[PDB]
Amino acid sequence: KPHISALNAPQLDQRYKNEFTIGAAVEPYQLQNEKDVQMLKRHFNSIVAENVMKPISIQPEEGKFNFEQADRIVKFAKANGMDIRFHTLVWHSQVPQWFFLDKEGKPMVNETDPVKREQNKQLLLKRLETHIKTIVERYKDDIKYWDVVNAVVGDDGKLRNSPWYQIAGIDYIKVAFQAARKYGGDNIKLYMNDYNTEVEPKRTALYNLVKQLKEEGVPIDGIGHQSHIQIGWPSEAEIEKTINMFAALGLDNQITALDVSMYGWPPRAYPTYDAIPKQKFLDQAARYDRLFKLYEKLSDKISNVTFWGIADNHTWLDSRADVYYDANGNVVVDPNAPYAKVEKGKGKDAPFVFGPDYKVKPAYWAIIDHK
Ligand SMILES: [Cl-]
Ligand SMILES: [Cl-]
Ligand SMILES: [Zn+2]
Ligand SMILES: [Zn+2]
Ligand SMILES: [Zn+2]
Ligand SMILES: [Zn+2]
Ligand SMILES: [Zn+2]
Ligand SMILES: [Zn+2]
Ligand SMILES: [Zn+2]
View 1 (tube, rainbow, N blue to C red):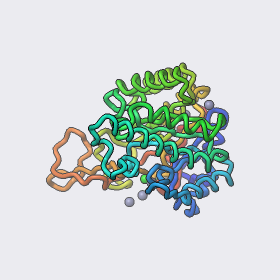
View 2 (cartoon, rainbow, N blue to C red; view 1 turned 180 degrees about the vertical axis):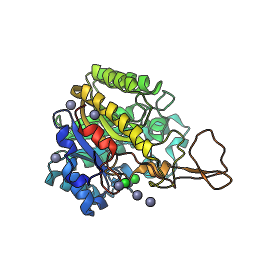
View 3 (cartoon, rainbow, N blue to C red; view 1 turned 90 degrees about the vertical axis):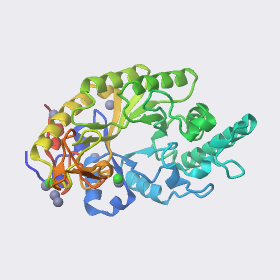
View 4 (tube, rainbow, N blue to C red; view 1 turned 90 degrees about the horizontal axis):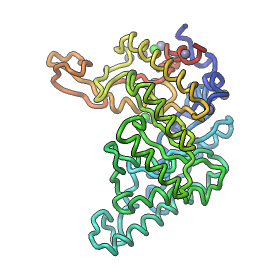
């Protein structure tokens, strides 16, 4: 099982073509990198924007729509027969602040008068509607899958108390889905996307929320499991229990941002790829082996498995890879060991089945086989 160039290795999407599509998250600049273009053409049949389709990238100022970057990803996908997932219509992260300012330019979260709070809610929902409308009216014939809302359940099992929720209550979620369905029609598929979907109390809160919304006729077709996981956690048994319970509600499941970190939480990362011991890649390959065997076992309930990146030279996990140093200046990776300082976001994670030099990893062989 050689570390051969991925560029000519057996195609990952083809291995799984009857089980679910295989996707990658990208930045438009990658569509200008020969290696990345050949990787997308060779191994993937589904794509998503790491960042350029988020709210702040699309409408940074009210009335100013920037579709130029998103368009590049849509054109490439269409020219290569790839499905597209839209990430994401609504999120509390880096949301353009203008959405949440009242007519006088003051934060709506601050309004204490009940009648002005009601007016802000209505103004906010109107803005939400127009953002969704403009985007879905442009892409309804091109993008099949949609993360309508992202991370709306808090890790405490209560609804995340973002400005969307403080200002508009639960209706912002119902409004977002109804608007996507109204302007995109019945053929686009609508998802509620979140991370740590396997973890209690968040899992049961998500389940109850979607069950309720569907009972009320809110159009929700599936759940997106970001799946930012570790080599050990969460267990395959809990992933399975999660996929199954949402599937029992009549919902499709898509793995939307998979990455298998080499670290725990908080991560104590190595400073370079070179420093990661070979054994960690073997541990990761066994995790990937078990994980995809499970996705295959549940393939009639999962329509897509998308990795949050292409190869290990580029992954958002690096922004979380903190490097701890002892007083002698040696790197510390044991979570319980002494350390003197930490360099936040300066280390290197290695989450995919393709290495930084675009050669296949042991995890690739573990999932391209049939054992
Ligand atoms: Cl990134
Ligand atoms: Cl390497
Ligand atoms: Zn293909
Ligand atoms: Zn190096
Ligand atoms: Zn290297
Ligand atoms: Zn295998
Ligand atoms: Zn499937
Ligand atoms: Zn990136
Ligand atoms: Zn290599």
